[PDB]
């Protein structure tokens, strides 16, 4: 979560292009950098979705095939089981450590063997199921008259289905893999992309960094600000603090300095006003 | 006939008395007889301007030297330190023939060549070019003070030139060379200037290079003969 902008930029380049470019001190070259990323991040606040809480932009967060959230459940039985597992670990002994070690060695061999020879390829059933999954995600947006699927989502489902097929050591990817891929993808969408303001998955969170609620509030604030300036339109210049007090005196929401300035910037990009220090001027 | 190169290198040939005298007479006659397209004598005017201002330095153009006396133009880049010596000796007596009192002002006159056709890039010099007359371009970065050098004493100055920025490829590094300025060439330039340099390519031994590389490798420098801004 707390890497700097240049690191974010080179990471974006690597994850999009799978190569890294260098030009320094007479050295000019291109390198192969096809690597699998696994990241751990931090801000909890249930009133806001993950991308709304953490620092990083949607350009990077939209690249992961799956996203997971880890927090305490406030469950007595969960604490009891966790403490019991901890007590069992306090008495951890060779009677089961050796068995876990043996299974770990066998698992390394299993992964190495599967990786060395197995190539899952498409089936008619898997193709139908994957097409249907994409159609389901497009249909989910149709009630709101909006986009809710695009090809990158289908790639995530395909990769997960191929991996599940390879776990079974199957040379065919098949409906067994796709239904599990849909399950994981749906669960991940539920946990990662739900708007806590409505309990519904809002794709614009993952593609723009905010709930559509924030967008609507910003637009309404800009229209209210425009109406306030127009109601005083006999004057060419209005004071910043006076406009802030007018808005905050007419709003139900406790509008912040950032919200007010974002609305001013939006109206400036719309060629309605110019902000000159402490004075707002009409165009 | 002067052209009869047999049994000798050109350096040895122009050292011989017969060829030396033929070269001397041919350049002198070229100076007195050369005419412009209008039928005007070129060097009467140029010598008179040189004398009136006490400047002691004569510029010649390679193109019309070739156009009228090609045999000398053919030898000139192959043995510059020989033909330039003969040329200096020939020019001084033409000057004294026109202006008999000019030995009061100076006892030597230097001939400087210009518009030499065989330009080379500052990184394309090779051992193929050693002890020949060349032309290159670049920007000055280092420039010593003017100092006196033994010979009698004469002015001496040393400079460093490198490839003009934006003529190197993007993101890579420039090459560079050292050059030597003697007599009336000093203070013909200052740092940051872009110049056109005509000179002799020359090399000598240096123990530092041999000990740094481990192979018997020599150092090189350019003796300037004509300098002009582009």
Image: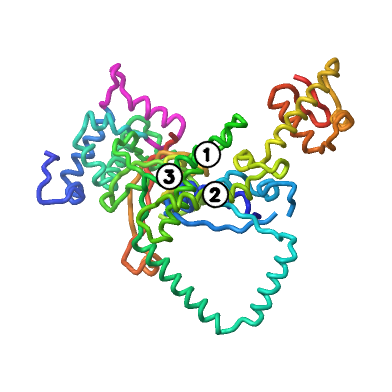
Tell me the quadrant of the picture where the N terminus of chain A can be found: bottom right
Instruction: Specify whether disc 3 shares its chain with disc 2.
Output: no
Instruction: Specify whether disc 3 shares its chain with disc 1.
Output: no
Spatial distance from mark 3 to mark 2, Cα to Cα? 59 Å
Local secondary structure at mark 2: helix
Q: What stretch is highlighted in magenta?
A: B33-58
Q: What residue is shown at x 18% (from left), y 39% (from top)?
A: B22
Tell whether label 2 touches label 3 (CB within 8 Å). Answer: no
Q: Where is residue A256 in the image (x, y as percent from the top left)?
A: 82, 38
Tell whether label 1 touches label 2 (CB within 8 Å). Answer: no
Of badges 3 and 1, the one in the foreground is 1
Regarding residue B184, the answer to whether it shows in the image is no
Residue A185 got which mark? 2
Quadrant location of residue A220? top right
Spatial distance from mark 2 to mark 1, Cα to Cα? 12 Å
Horizontal placement of A246 versus A22: left or right? right
Q: How crowded is mark 2: few (under 14 residues within 10 Å), some or many (20 or more)?
A: some
Q: Mark 3 points at which residue?
A: B163
Is residue A191 highlighted in magenta?
A: no
Q: Where is residue B60 in the image (x, y as percent from the top left)?
A: 33, 33
Regarding residue A191, the answer to whether it shows in the image is yes
Tell me the quadrant of the picture where the C terminus of chain A can be found: top right
Q: Position of residue B6 (x, y in %)?
A: 10, 47
Local secondary structure at mark 1: helix
Q: Name the residue under label 1.
A: A136
Tell whether label 1 touches label 3 (CB within 8 Å). Answer: no
Determine the chain carrying the residue at label 2. A
Above or below, B93 relative to A102: above
Determine the chain carrying the residue at label 3. B
């Amino acid at each position: 979560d707390k890497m700097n902008e240049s690191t974010r930029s080179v990471l974006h380049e690597v994850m999009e292009q799978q190569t890294l470019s260098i030009a320094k001190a007479g050295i000019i070259c291109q390198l192969n950098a096809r690597t699998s990323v696994l990241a751990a991040a931090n801000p909890w606040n249930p009133k806001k979705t993950t991308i709304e809480n953490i620092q990083l932009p949607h350009t990077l967060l939209s690249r992961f095939d799956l996203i997971f959230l880890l927090l305490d459940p406030q469950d007595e039985a969960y604490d009891r089981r966790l403490a019991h597992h901890l007590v069992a670990l306090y008495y951890q002994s060779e009677e089961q450590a050796e068995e876990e070690l043996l299974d770990m060695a066998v698992l390394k061999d299993y992964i190495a063997y599967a990786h060395s020879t197995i190539m899952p390829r498409l089936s008619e059933e898997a193709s139908q199921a994957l097409i249907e999954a994409y159609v389901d995600m497009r249909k989910i947006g149709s009630s709101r008259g909006m986009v809710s699927a695009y090809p990158r989502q289908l790639e995530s489902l395909i990769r997960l289905a191929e991996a599940h097929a390879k776990v079974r050591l199957s040379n065919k990817v098949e409906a067994i893999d796709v239904e599990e891929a849909k399950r994981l993808h749906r669960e991940a969408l539920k946990q990662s992309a739900t708007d806590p303001r409505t309990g519904i998955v809002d794709i614009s969170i993952l593609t723009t960094g905010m709930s559509a609620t924030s967008r609507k509030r910003k637009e309404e604030l800009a229209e209210a600000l425009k109406k306030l300036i127009l109601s005083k339109g006999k004057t060419p210049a209005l004071k910043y603090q006076q406009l802030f007090e007018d808005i905050r005196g007419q709003s139900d929401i406790a509008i912040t300095k950032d919200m007010f300035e974002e609305a001013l910037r939006a109206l400036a990009d719309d060629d309605f006003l110019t902000v000159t220090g402490k004075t707002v001027r009409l165009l | 006939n002067l052209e009869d190169l047999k049994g000798h290198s050109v350096r040895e040939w122009v050292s011989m008395a017969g060829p030396r005298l033929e070269i001397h007479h041919r350049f002198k006659n070229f100076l007195r007889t050369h005419v412009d397209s209008h039928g005007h004598n070129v060097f009467k005017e140029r010598i008179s301007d040189m004398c009136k201002e006490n400047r002691e330095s004569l510029v010649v153009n390679y193109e019309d030297l070739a156009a009228r006396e090609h045999v000398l133009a053919y030898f000139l880049p192959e043995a510059p330190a020989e033909l330039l010596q003969i040329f200096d000796e020939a020019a001084l007596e033409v000057v004294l023939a026109m202006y008999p009192k000019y030995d009061r002002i100076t006892n030597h006159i230097h001939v400087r060549i210009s518009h030499l056709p065989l330009v080379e890039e500052l990184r394309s010099l090779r051992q193929l070019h050693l002890n020949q007359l060349i032309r290159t371009s670049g920007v000055v970065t280092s420039c010593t003070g003017v100092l006196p050098q033994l010979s009698i004493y004469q002015n001496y100055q040393r400079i460093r030139i490198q490839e003009s920025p934006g003529k190197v490829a993007a993101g890579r590094l420039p090459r560079s060379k050292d050059a030597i300025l003697l007599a009336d060439l000093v203070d013909s330039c200052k740092p940051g200037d872009e110049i056109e340099l005509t000179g002799i390519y020359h090399n000598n031994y240096d123990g530092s290079l041999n000990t740094a590389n481990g192979f018997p490798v020599f150092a090189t420098v350019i003796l300037a003969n004509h300098v002009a801004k582009k």
